[PDB]
Image: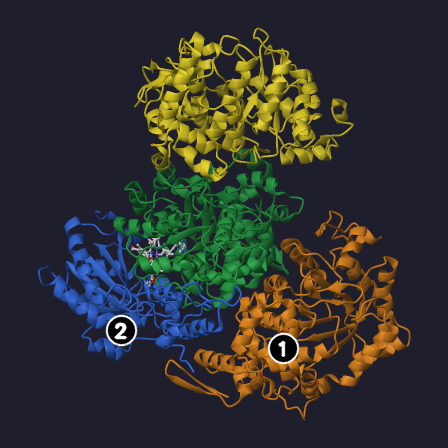
Chain colours: A green, B yellow, C orange, D blue
Amino acid sequence: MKLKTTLFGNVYQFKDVKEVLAKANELRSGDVLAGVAAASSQERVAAKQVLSEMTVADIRNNPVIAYEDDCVTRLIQDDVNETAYNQIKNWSISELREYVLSDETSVDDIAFTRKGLTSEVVAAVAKICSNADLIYGAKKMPVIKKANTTIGIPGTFSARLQPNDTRDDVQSIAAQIYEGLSFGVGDAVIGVNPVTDDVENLSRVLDTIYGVIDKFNIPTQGCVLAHVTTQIEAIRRGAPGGLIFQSICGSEKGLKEFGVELAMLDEARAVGAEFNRIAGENCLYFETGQGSALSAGANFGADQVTMEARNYGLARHYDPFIVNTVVGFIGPEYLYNDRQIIRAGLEDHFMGKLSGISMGCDCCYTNHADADQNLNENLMILLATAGCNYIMGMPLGDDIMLNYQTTAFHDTATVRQLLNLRPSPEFERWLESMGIMANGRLTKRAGDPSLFF
Amino acid sequence: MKLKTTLFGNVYQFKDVKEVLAKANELRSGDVLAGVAAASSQERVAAKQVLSEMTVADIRNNPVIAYEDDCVTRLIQDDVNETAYNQIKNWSISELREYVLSDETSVDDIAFTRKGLTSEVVAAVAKICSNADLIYGAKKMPVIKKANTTIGIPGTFSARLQPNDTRDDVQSIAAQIYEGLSFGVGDAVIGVNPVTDDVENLSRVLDTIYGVIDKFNIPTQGCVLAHVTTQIEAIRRGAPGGLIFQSICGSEKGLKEFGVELAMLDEARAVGAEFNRIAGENCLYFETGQGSALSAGANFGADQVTMEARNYGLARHYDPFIVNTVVGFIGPEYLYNDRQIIRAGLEDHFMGKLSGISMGCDCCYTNHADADQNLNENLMILLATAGCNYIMGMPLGDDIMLNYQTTAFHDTATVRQLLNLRPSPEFERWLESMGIMANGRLTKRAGDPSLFF
Amino acid sequence: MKLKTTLFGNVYQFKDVKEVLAKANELRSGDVLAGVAAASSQERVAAKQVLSEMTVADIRNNPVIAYEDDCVTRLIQDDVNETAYNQIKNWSISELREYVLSDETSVDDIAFTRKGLTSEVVAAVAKICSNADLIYGAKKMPVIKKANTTIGIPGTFSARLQPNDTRDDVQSIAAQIYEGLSFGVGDAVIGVNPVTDDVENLSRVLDTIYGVIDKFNIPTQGCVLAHVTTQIEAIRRGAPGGLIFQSICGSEKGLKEFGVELAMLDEARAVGAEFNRIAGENCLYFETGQGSALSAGANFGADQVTMEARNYGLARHYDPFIVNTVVGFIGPEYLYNDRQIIRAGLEDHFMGKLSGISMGCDCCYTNHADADQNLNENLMILLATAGCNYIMGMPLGDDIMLNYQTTAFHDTATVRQLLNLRPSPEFERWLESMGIMANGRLTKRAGDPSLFF
Amino acid sequence: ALDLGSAEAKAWIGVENPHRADVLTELRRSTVARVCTGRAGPRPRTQALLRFLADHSRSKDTVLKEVPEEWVKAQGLLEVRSEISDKNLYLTRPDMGRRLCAEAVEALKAQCVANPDVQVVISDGLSTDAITVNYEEILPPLMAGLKQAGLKVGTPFFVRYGRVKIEDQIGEILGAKVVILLVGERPGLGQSESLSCYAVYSPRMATTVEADRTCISNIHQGGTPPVEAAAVIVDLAKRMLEQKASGINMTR
Ligand code: COY
């Protein structure tokens, strides 16, 4: 493989694949913090060209953390369909980009080709894509999964109802649920991040969620986003099982930071099959986002985009119902502003769909980042055009506990009515029964939580 | 439990669940041979009534072969969703029959309900269903799988091309392939039962099948129906992998008779993931049929319907692309005539769809059985209305090597055009491109294998 | 009037309507340069609240430049439907925002309501709208015009072919024309900004544009974007007239800077009626953009958003076929970065649609501004979802002569295929006849200018 | 006229023509979340959007504000800092926020007690308001809980510009068996006084992972009351000594 190019008479030398992958990234504060970013726009482009000229084989055989040192690398590499790999191993990343974007490449062609990819190759394609490349490429790669609702069907747009409270108060949780359902939010999941990671508390939160689900026969699923171990334990004790959640990272050390072993995720599948109230075949839920590996000291000299793609390689193995990047969840140290957050969200969603997972995005930012709510509204619409499977829904987008701003309930309704998108067909049916939705649009009585009383 | 009822003033006493299950069956040759059949028509009805009043719990807790002695029973029992089971355990088999047939019961309702079932419960429901119950019940339970084609979508009907030869001659296999395709047969699979169970011959037959697939870019998959161990070896040594086949039985003793361990089916799953040319997520293929357990001395005093249902509970664990009963493959000793073959075929298909597998049927009879080709045409049409995922296809239905008669290539075209059913959407598009199909109908130039030359 | 509010216990006092309008704007470079921007984020919100509580009458009666001193103000004020105005004069700007965004407000409701508005009122509503408000609001306000093509029908998306050259070389102009058409660009207009502002050169460029139009019978119109006086002369002396162009400004001083009298636009209207090859009733074409008034010293202490809205009030009087903002044409001094360009673009488009003009947008940036091509791709997609009537098209977006980057020909095809939008119905039919388009999608032979040879 | 920061503005119901209007008041009272604001089409109502923007401007100011040097000195605390110099650097360099500066290491060895059983550490983190409002309510009952009916207590000190991982260095240098860190969480939209507690048993720079810590979050008057939270942290500290474990390694 060639590790150098000439640009405007100047030679641009690179030491390894990991460096080329890093410097080909568009500028972000996290890559500068990791010391892996390009020195200039010229070096960035030269890195993109070197990357584009490298083969799938060059990148598959050079994962950022070695096979023997990382269980996630082993997981990713051993899931490869080697026949699919052999067909594409001599393709340049330039050729792979053009193949993904081609109108002569069908959904079924990509279904087989993606099986010969590794996460590093997925990231490599994303790095040589413009914003519209990432949007259009993702759109022609739909991923459909099924719990009690079907998510990912082109022409549809789902939403996680996120009814969070500072004290896990069941009245405050219910009120946000009723408000969310009134806007048609909740077809992805009704998922609460709990304050106390406690078995008795999880059961009470779940019973509140399922108290509403059972009362109105809602086709959906509940979830409590504690550590996977306490979810498993509570469900084993008889708490209602919908989706089982875990935050994942793209390295073994990153998973050890979260207190996760691969055996726990396998156990989550088995507990779900034995206990969970899910009609379909998918019941797992993961969240991701750029910067997490670097935060854990677990990026090993690799950029955050490549590490983020490794998440999707790991997630794919467990065939989850939904995955979303939580794009601006952490802070300005990994993604500084509007520009970087938008780019990351488009990258994350593109890579998720190329990896073949049910990919959504929590369009978000923090109050210490150079951003505002107009960023969320910009990104959610761009991502919805890319066929993003789901976003979050909170009252006005204000999380009273997690201390950040996501998308409003209003925003899902806006996106759906703007782009003529429907909810999950099962959930849509229920919304019509309740008189909340007619022909994809909120009725006059919608947006009013008192309708349920 | 009640193992007793009074009918017309006469008390009928039954020993156990196994006897109730056996005697509730409609009269068939195999059950008489097994000595488990009813003595009279009144006792048959008595057993039906006793079975109908028994609960799901009664049948689930009493499998025909014990948990500790049978790995198939273990696999069936351990796959149960206990939350689903607990909702329905106090239901009578009569109530479950009415639940399956009800128009208020949706596809998604059965999706969750069936996870609380075992194969014996599946069998029990079938035993108290009339022929139209079996047809209507199966129809409202579609099962959709995807390899390189999608099978089981309502309004579609697929077909296995079975180009068998007496010497595995490649000219004879190819000739039948071109004939079948010209009628629109082969969307399920192009599957050859080989004469010689060895690696080089399997590799030659697969190269012949895939020579056709590659030349005309056919969206389909190949299969050589040898023993699973020989297929695995051929595939590992470089032969093109499509579907991996294994004949299965409803008991550990039965599997030992065929020389199969559950680890081989696990291995096939893993080998498929690494090597097979399959775009979708399903690649296994099983064949089943009533009488095989009784032939093996592996029915353990149980009837052939219940044993056949256990095949589907076993198959379900491995989430195969396709399963079919080979309804009258063996002989009159297990299924005597037209009546019994039709009944068995409807039972098998209904039980497979209830078990959540991609259930098709080889509509067939042997020459020493009391049947003819008109039987095959009666059954194929009835099963097609039940939403049978696929049938076989051979030139006029004559297997020149397995020595039996199945359905003709003509029969698939007939069923499609009679019932306004389409092929697999991917394969249909290929047929339209080849000028073989227009609007679900064969064109003038169709039915002519020389079209490919 | 209230020119005061209290926020967090702090009293914020404003001098006049002009200051309230200016400070309510989202932060941008031009407003700081003008010295009219807010001092803090709290004062920005204070100005937003003060503006929202002001009535339509408050804003209508206080234009930024006086009636007696400004012919643009006079034209805006005299065009008002007083019956419409009287119905809404006591409405707060907050109530008018809610009225525009409401799903109970139909296209015909806004049709009458907007006639009681002035440009300052249009601007005021925009200032208290979030990014998604601007997008959704504009989307439910379609504006349809017709030349030789119809533009602005919901579900359609047009494009200006901009084949500019450094020497007005006819081979270079034609080459870009064939390239643009091969991507389906040119339904809005084929418009050239000329190097030399003289009659013979304009006549030569128009003959080149119309040489292509006549040879392939293209339903479209040509335009040379010189000064209106030179276009008029060329047309009167026999050059083919399509659209007549003029750059406009929001003040009399601003128009004098460009060297335009309102009588010239009246003359263009009359010249168009006598000479132009236009089937429909619309033939004028204006371009606008924030900062131009401030550049001319003609903003009179007012912000660039309000001044840009006055452009649309002026344009409306002349009922043009198309108007577009050239969002980031000037430099960082008026719009600094990605954020500000996106915001301005959404504002401009929303305000144009509210004013009832056929509003499009040149999604663009300059090389001395803090932006890149990914900005153009973000904005073009967002505006397309807002129902933007048209964007520009140039080979890769590189203007080799105006020295800026706009949207690529590729981008129009991308937006259309991403969002299932069609070209102008007349032009779409031409593309289908040429074998360039099928079902809204580019064919295999499309994207190739040699197709015309 | 209305102040967007006032109680009436926060309690505002914007739902037009409600199905059951007494339920909406009961829903607005049951939660601090921005519920019952109604809509204009699928978009938020103007007043709700204004209140959102007003609370954002206040939230932006609340993040770059600093605890005065005089305030910490008045609380009788040692002020020490990380490798970070100012607020701007703190927001972009988390790695420097995780390490004490050279003069900080020396000051801790000089002025703090050696080998304590429980070490209490306070840091501004991402919110100065979190430690300002809650301090007098949380810190005194924490000390009167750990000492009274307890064991060896370290001296409390303030870390300026600190991140959670810095308690690992603090545990090694001081030889602490249990390190308690009271730190300001990133500020929310309409609320910025939310404090967190991070506790770890015998930490090491090269072995301790984040899962080894126990988190007590949302400590404020709107969450877990600082006085009530103080007794929770004491009990946690006692359980951590008894089990010789923290975080995921603990029982129940
Ligand atoms: C930001 C944040 C994070 C992030 C860490 C910060 C970073 N990487 O720089 C993030 C995204 C990695 C994250 C992950 C998790 C994981 C794992 C944490 C671990 N063991 O490493 C987590 C276990 C989720 C899961 N189920 O797997 C988790 C949880 C449950 C919690 C909760 C703790 C419950 C409890 N009582 O134990 C929690 C209170 C929220 C809640 N659910 O109510 C919160 C502390 C919840 C917090 C809510 C709140 N109200 O405070 C919140 C919002 C802010 C904390 C803060 O402001 N700290 C102050 C700041 C100055 O400290 P700092 O030094 O800069 O940062 C440190 C701490 O934040 C610490 N830390 C953060 N979380 C956390 C949890 C525990 C138990 C411990 C001991 C220490 C923890 O890690 C860093 C070390 O540098 C937060 N987190 Co986390 C909330 C989870 C978010 C949803 C999924 N998610 C979002 N984005 C991404 C992503 N990119 N990838 C994957 N997943 C996600 N968090 N979290 N988190």
Label 1 CB, ligand 1: below 8 Å?
no
Residue A332 figure quarter: bottom left
- Residue furthest to the left: D149
Tell me if B125 is positioned left or right of A9 in this view: left
Q: Residue at x 74, y 53 (%)?
A: C447
Tell me the subunit letter for badge 2.
Answer: D
Labels 1, 2: one chain? no
Q: Answer above or below: position of A347 versus B266.
A: below
* Rendered-image quadrant of the C terminus of chain A: bottom left
Check disc 1 and report the residue beneath it: C290
Q: Residues within 10 Å of mark 2 (few under 14, many from 20)?
A: some
Tell me if D8 is positioned left or right of A57 in this view: left
Q: Answer above or below: position of B407 versus D21.
A: above
Tell me if C59 is positioned left or right of B248 in this view: right
Residue D131 figure quarter: bottom left
Gap between marks 1 and 2 measured at Cα? 45 Å
- Residue furthest to the bottom: C68
Quadrant of picture, ligand 1:
bottom left
Q: Amino acid at mark 1?
A: Gln
| Callout 2 secondary element | helix
Q: Residue C371, can we see it?
A: no
Tag count: 2
Q: Residue at x 23, y 75 (%)?
A: D72
For residue A446, which numbered disc appears in the image? Answer: none
User: Answer yes or no: do the residues labelled 1 and 2 have beta carbons within 8 Å?
Assistant: no
Q: Residue A188, can we see it?
A: yes
Q: Amino acid at mark 2?
A: Thr
Counting from the top left corner in percent of width and height, residue A326 is at: 44, 56
Check disc 2 and report the residue beneath it: D132
Q: Residues within 10 Å of mark 1 (few under 14, many from 20)?
A: many
Tell me the subunit letter for badge 1.
Answer: C
